[PDB]
Image (tube, rainbow, N blue to C red; front, side):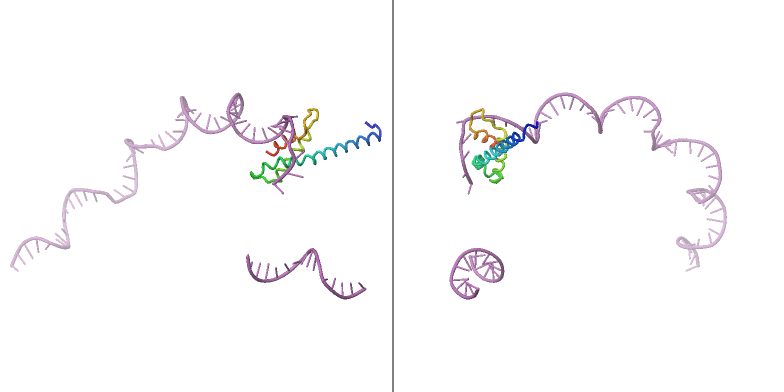
Length: 86
DNA sequence: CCAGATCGTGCGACACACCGGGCCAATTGGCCGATGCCGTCCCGCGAACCCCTCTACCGTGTTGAGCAGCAGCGGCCT
């Protein structure tokens, strides 16, 4: 749909804002991954490898999160982070 | 001295020498032909085997020695 240039600009701006929001959520939640991954230390894999795998798990969780359930975001992220790490 | 061993000689036997015949025994060894059991394969189903996915009270920090180059500083020079 052609729509109007101003509406297209506004839609692009909100899309960029949503991308920024996703990023911001990821940086805010990296500390949770770091906290979770420290109790699996040893057993071959090193600390930073575990942290990065947990980061991938957290990204996956953020890709599939909803707020209608009225629960704090830490729970879903914790489940997925532990699953990915193990 | 003279009589048997050795050998000469002789007669016979004769064990085969031949080189050629004319049949035979034993013993075949092929698979002929007919009959029968095993290797291969093509499913058929099912046990297991490996991979992927998701869970929402919440939870937010791991010696000695030798030789050479670089950083800081005292002190001219402008």
